[PDB]
């Protein structure tokens, strides 16, 4: 047995939307907060759980991505680089300009043994944010000395 999905044949930037203010509402729009809230506290095991539910709902295509890149963050902390890497990609394919998943993806790769790649992803982070130095450095951090 197996499952899947294909399409992404839609084009559009997106649009914001309001949200209710009350506990219990397990709506990706609201519940989502639960994830970050747990992250800013350190609780990784939980933070992820929240992000999971959110993705397991009828959320917008612009929000589904933000969650993907978020899932990785949790993994990385939970010695889940292997997965973290993949997750990131899912958030990169959705849009493409998500440097967030990129900066995180590299971190995972470096552990997997794929350096060259870690650099490629970063190189992109510099484009999106021509000011964010964190990238200009993170690159040389894994690029190390030149050989050959």
Image: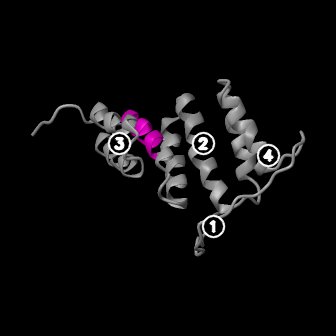
Q: Which mark is residue 118?
A: 3
Q: Colour scheme in the image?
A: one colour
Q: What number is the disc on residue 70?
A: 2
What percent of the width, then of the height, locates residue 45?
A: 68, 30
Distance from the alpha carbon under mark 4 to that under mark 2: 15 Å
**Labels 2 and 3: the sequence-earlier one:** 2
Mark 2 burial class by Cα count in 10 Å: few <14, some 14-19, many 20+: many
Q: Which of 16 and 116 lies nearest the eye of the viewer?
A: 16
Return the disc, 4 or 3, that comes first in the chain's sequence.
Answer: 4
Q: Position of residue 20 (x, y in %)?
A: 86, 49
Query: CB of mark 2 within 8 Å of CB of mark 3?
Result: no
Disc 4 to disc 3, C-alpha distance: 33 Å
Q: Name the secondary structure under disc 2.
A: helix
User: Magenta segment range?
Assistant: 102-111
Q: For mark 4, does the 10 Å Cα neighbourhood hold few (<14), some (14 to 19), or many (20 or more) residues?
A: some
Q: Is residue 136 above or below residue 67?
A: above
């Amino acid at each position: 047995g197996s499952s899947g999905s294909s399409g992404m044949t839609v084009s559009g930037p997106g649009t914001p939307e309001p949200r209710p203010a009350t506990p219990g509402a397990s709506s990706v729009e609201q519940l989502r907060k639960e994830g970050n809230e747990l992250f800013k506290c350190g609780d990784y095991g939980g933070a992820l759980a929240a992000y999971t539910q959110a993705l397991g709902l009828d959320a917008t295509p612009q929000d589904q991505a933000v969650l993907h890149r978020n899932r990785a963050a949790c993994h990385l902390k939970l010695e889940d680089y292997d997965k973290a890497e993949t997750e990131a990609s899912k958030a990169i394919e959705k849009d493409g300009g998500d440097v967030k998943a990129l900066y995180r993806r590299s971190q995972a790769l470096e552990k997997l043994g794929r350096l060259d790649q870690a650099v490629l992803d970063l190189q992109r982070c510099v484009s999106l944010e021509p000011k964010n130095k964190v990238f200009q450095e993170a690159l040389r951090n894994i690029s190390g000395p030149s050989s050959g």
